[PDB]
Length: 192
Ligand SMILES: CCOc1ccc(Br)c([C@@H](CN)OB2O[C@@H]3[C@H](O2)[C@@H](COP(=O)(O)O)O[C@H]3n2cnc3c(N)ncnc32)c1
Image 1: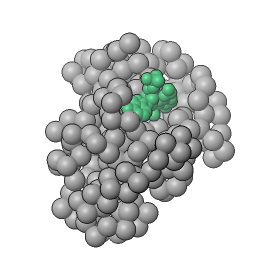
Image 2: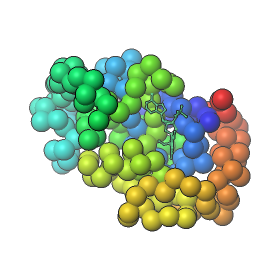
Image 3: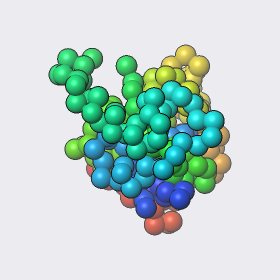
C-alpha cells in the first residue's frame, strides 16, 4: 500500500490506502470519530445549502460531532458487528492528484487504532465507500474500467480512466506511477 497526505483547504491528513492507483477517484475523506485532528478541522458553521443528511440534525458541526460521538457510545458489540452513518466536519481537504476539494467526514466504519485512523474514500472501487456514498449522496467516480459502478463498487484489475497521467495503465502499473508521483512531490510513501 501507500500513505498519502491530503492538505486542509483552510494541517495535513495522512491516509493509508491499499489502492493508491485510485487516487483520482477519491471523492471524500473519512476520519475515525476519535481521530486527533477532528476537533481542529471542525468548521464553526455549515456551508449554505448543505445536504441535511450530512449534519446529523446538529445546528453546527461541533454540536453534530459531539452528538455523533455520544450516540455511537450507545452502540453495543451487536451493532459494531452488523448501515453507514457519519457526519460532515463542515470542512474540505485537497485531493493531491486532481487538486479538487473533497469534504471531510467522521464515520464509525473507520477505526481509530488502525493504519493512520483515516482513509481516502473511493466509492467507485471500495464497496464500503460505495455504500456510504450512496447513503449520503456523495460523488461516485469510475477510475478503473472493468465493472459497472452503477451496480456496485468494481474491486478488480482493469485499466485506468479519468486519471490524467495514469490513463490506460493497468492497476499494478498505476500503483507504481502514483507512488512515484507522491514521492516526487514529497506527499506520500509506499508502505507494507
Ligand atoms: C482492504 C481493501 O481496501 C481497499 C479496497 C479498495 C479501495 Br479503492 C481502497 C482505498 C479506498 N477506500 O483505500 B483502501 O481502504 C483503506 C485501506 O485501503 C484498507 C487497508 O486495509 P488492510 O490494512 O486490511 O489491508 O482498508 C481501509 N482502511 C485503512 N485504514 C482504515 C481504518 N483505520 N479503518 C477502516 N478502514 C481502513 C481500499
